[PDB]
Length: 96
Length: 139
Length: 166
Image (cartoon, chains in turn orange, brown, red):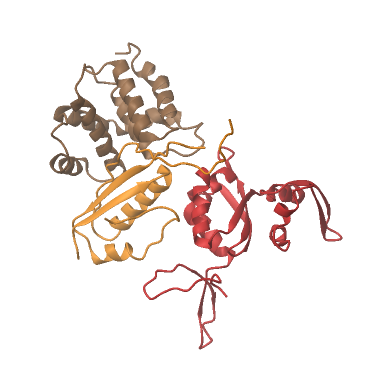
């Protein structure tokens, strides 16, 4: 069943990704197995510029966090729910 | 005055208690997995055990302390803020070897590096309104 | 006609849609799915923003012209949360992802108001409204625009303000 399962989890907004993490914990606990994580990462800022006109003579810090989910004993219902769910637009649910 | 092992143990305790309060499992099994599968070579073992035991025995105590300070929040209460406030108030309730300003400084560092860019002022406000009440001596 | 006019998928593409119609007695097509109706936009704002489903923000009205322009009205119940500032989100990072779903379609997230004239004033968010004379007996709402702000308010074929009518 490819039992060695790695998940990294990106977070721009912490509330939306905590909601998605609670949904992952729910859809992992309602199928039989037990889930581990997140063990979160500290503040990893980004280097992203804006499209603004230059001055003739915004944002700089993007607080992104990472979360870790390890699965070692899955079921077929667990991976089915991981292949029959829906998510919010713009966030990553990448099962590494 | 303190090495980096105490800071690493404190950050790993923040991660382990957030994982416990969000995954909602047994504290002993998650603690054994976190001590036998993660980076624990620079983690103080006794600090980790005493901090997690104090948080686990004062869940309801720190929730009763947090309950009068959940009114003026614009959004609802998050989990990272709750973990930072629980660990910060247990480090300002019964810990004698950790100083007052040192625990407040480490709590502000944890709230700025883990909570949000806007929730660390909430953490500092709850600490400034709770730590003179819990510790009038400020030790 | 239920899809976007430029959708040409391939075998092995998880596409997302909304069941809207059913005819169980009919032998033919019995489960109608859409991607270009505004109930899809209602479901996108329900999945994206949690507090709309948590009975904080009230979405009552919406209208679209797919791929180009759309409007939607929100209304808060908790005064502690800005409805437009949260449904737009931080830097517009939410609805732009919704713009990923609709392909560049500019979605005006505006504030619902009980007064219809002040609601239309709030509804022209990339535009400016001077004064509105409402005569519902003659079924008219005469809207005054400022000079120079005609092309950004009207846009293409007068549609989006008509969408504001919708």
